[PDB]
Amino acid sequence: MLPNMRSALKMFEQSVLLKSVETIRVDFVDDIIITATPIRAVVQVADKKKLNLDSLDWSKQYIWVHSGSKMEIGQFIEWHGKDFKLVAAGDDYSDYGYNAWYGEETLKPVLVSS
Amino acid sequence: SQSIINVARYIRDLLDYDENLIQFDRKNTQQSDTVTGYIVVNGSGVQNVLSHGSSYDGDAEIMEYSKSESRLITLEFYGSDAYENAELFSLLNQSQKAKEVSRGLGLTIYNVSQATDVKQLLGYQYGNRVHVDFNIQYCPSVYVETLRVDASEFEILVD
Image 1 (cartoon, chains in turn purple, red):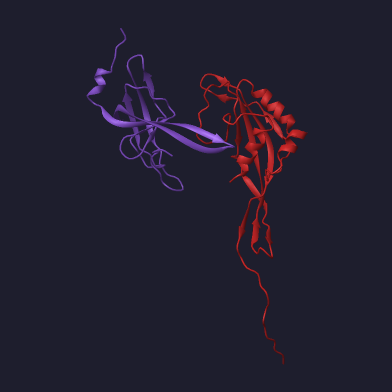
Image 2 (cartoon, rainbow over the protein chains, first blue to last red):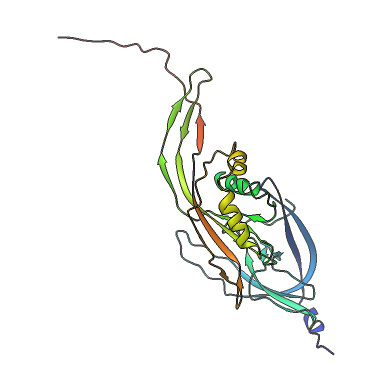
């Protein structure tokens, strides 16, 4: 019997939107439909969000979510005001009943429907 | 602007090759299923200008600021059939098909300069990846509504 952290994930839940992009192109012109779903999750900070140095300073908040629902990389997660690309340090205890990912705020505005 | 997309067009229908399988460059795009031989028009090479034209039109009176330039755009082929899509491109580049399909793509096309089978470190594995080089030369333009001079009144003086 595979251990299932699922029940150990409900208490800490939070509502959040999980979107994915399925890019569409004709004659090499970019359009992006969206797929958004209300999914369960839990959020903690992932890399303490610092200020990098460049020609202009920039900063991207990091969150790392858990959920009972599967989360592929090429998906975004919005919880407060800015979606996070599910890019890094993710791991799928799918057979153990959940999965986790870090998150990168796409400083672009949130993909509502396009 | 449009130049990289144009060379992407040219490689799109020189190899008779797919839309969704040509991605541009160092953008964000996932390369899933390594064997799906992709082609990417790497434009990271510095584009350097050559001249800055300036033409002027009389009747439908506006003028025309042009800027000829060139960039060493490289092509990276991926996938199990990378080698072929390299060579078969690196050799059809100077045929009828290419030189006949790049009609309106306001973009010259020079010979393929060099190739390389530099693969990519796909994490304890090697995925086929080949670069081919060729300088590409084009010229963006813009049009501006200036206005002509119809006459010139003036006065002279003398000792």
